[PDB]
Length: 143
Ligand SMILES: [Zn+2]
Image 1 (tube, rainbow, N blue to C red):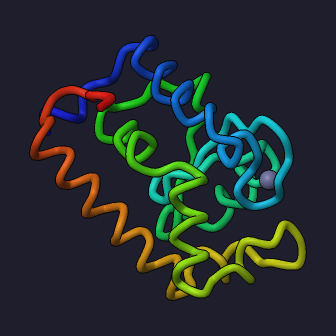
Image 2 (image 1 turned 180 degrees about the vertical axis):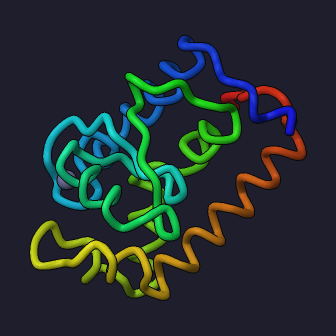
């Protein structure tokens, strides 16, 4: 549980700075609104304020949200964005015949985030996060 301490603001900023270099991470993963600063932590994706409200209403059983710029981030939570982000998520969905779920319109979020491809992705990302916790138990190392 060495990774449950809160990360420093500069580490938090550098994490989201790194994601921000990829264009996929500059648009909301659910609706494509520009410059999302909210997040769905378990899926490691960036969300606009509106979709942060959609996710919040789904319940913690499915997701929970945090602001990249207004909330304190734990080490373990930041890991999901070192290793995740919108580009990694989208690439997994494309490979796992789930491009229909990536549309910015006419997709219900609960269906999106409880689908098989979504559940396999969270497991995929969870393994990467567990490996990172074992190699880097108390600190967030960018490469
Ligand atoms: Zn959105």
